[PDB]
Image (cartoon, rainbow, N blue to C red):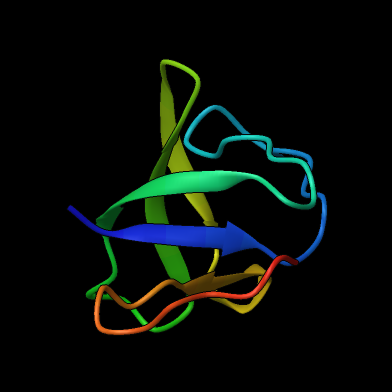
Length: 65
């Protein structure tokens, strides 16, 4: 299972999007598109800009953000 870190807060602009707070660790559902990634935040799924999150590779130990 993949995870991404919210680099900044993001307020959903429409029902297909989701809201996230800076520092959130979200479950990454789809990253095939280069601009919008589909993620899961507290029982909610939707797209967020790929620019606003960083994938946390399993192969790496991640420092505290």
